[PDB]
């Protein structure tokens, strides 16, 4: 990217998505597709689109803060103490540094992410 | 304030106790801002919340930080230094890179979620 050109996040059909799988699977066989939209701050900042199929898996954001904006489908985030957060298209949230809750995806979900490494 | 084991949800409902502001580089129309901070982290490095502007135009200057914007209501145009026009409306997400100096043109009213990371 260049300092004088706005970077738009394309929420249309994913171009050359990267395949992935959760590193902390719980249940089901969730698989991921990601497209990076932006990289800056000498490797410390990244943004793009991510998709998951059904399943459950644990987060660990030790070392970074992540903003999420659900754009399609739905999921539940369940904090370590059991507090359930139902998220659906249009919902925005932040996983603070060192967040270790889990994702439960009944069907399908897509989000925009913005990550800042500390 | 926040805790590492509690998800932080950004309230996109009515602005509660917003802080009033004005553009640093107004162009035309006396745009007036309201901001509500949702999150502060990384010992001053990261801030996120909701921001609104009334009609008008103003020039940005993001020297020292990267800003993610997600339009949640209304619409605007962002015009890059070279004249490239970006029409933005509800649901559109974009990033102003560090040192961005394009301008905003708000015909009526616009509201966005912002996430800023200082460099």
Image: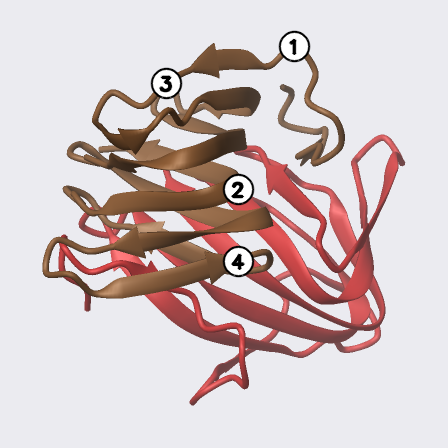
Chain colours: A brown, B red
Q: Position of residue A67 (x, y in %)?
A: 41, 46
Question: Around disc 1, counting alpha carbons within 10 Å, would you say few (fewer than 14), some (14 to 19), or many (20 or more)?
Answer: few
Q: Which chain does the numbered disc 4 sit on?
A: A
Above or below — where is B59 with respect to B53? Answer: above
- Residue that mark 4 sits on: A88
Q: Residue at x 27, y 63 (%)?
A: A84
- Residue A95, above or below B48: above
- What is the total number of numbered labels drawn onto the structure image? 4
- How far apart are the two marked residues, 1 and 4, measured between alpha carbons? 25 Å
In this image, A77 relative to B62: left or right? left
- Where residue B1 sits in the image (x, y, percent)? 19, 68
Query: What is the secondary structure assignment of the residue under circle 4?
Result: strand
Snapshot quadrant of residue B86? top right
Q: Which residue is mark 2?
A: A109
For marks 4 and 3, the one nearer the N-term is 3
Q: Are marks 1 and 3 on the same chain?
A: yes
User: Marks 3 and 2, Cα distance to the nearest angstrom?
Assistant: 14 Å
Which residue matches tag 1?
Answer: A16
Q: Is residue A112 above or below residue B107?
A: above
**Closer-to-camera residue (A43/B3):** B3
Task: Point out residue A101 in the picture as x, y percentages from the top left corner.
Answer: 20, 47
Whether residue B101 is visible, yes or no, is yes
Gap in angstroms between the C-alphas marked 4 and 2? 8 Å
Disc 1 chain ID: A
Q: Are marks 4 and 2 in contact (CB under 8 Å)?
A: no
Can residue B63 be seen? no
Residue at numbered disc 3? A21
């Amino acid at each position: 990217h260049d300092k004088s050109r706005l970077v738009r996040i394309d929420t249309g059909p994913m171009i050359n998505p990267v395949a992935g799988k959760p590193s902390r699977p719980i249940a089901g066989d969730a698989s991921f597709r990601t497209v990076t939209a932006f990289e800056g701050g000498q490797g410390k900042v990244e943004s793009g689109v991510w998709e998951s199929t059904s399943g459950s898996f644990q987060s660990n954001t030790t070392g970074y803060i992540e903003y999420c904006h659900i754009i399609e489908g739905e999921a539940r985030l369940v904090d370590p103490d059991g507090t359930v957060h139902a998220v659906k298209a249009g919902d925005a949230f932040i996983m603070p540094e060192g967040y270790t809750g889990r994702w439960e995806v009944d069907r399908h979900v897509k989000k925009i992410y913005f990550v800042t490494h500390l």
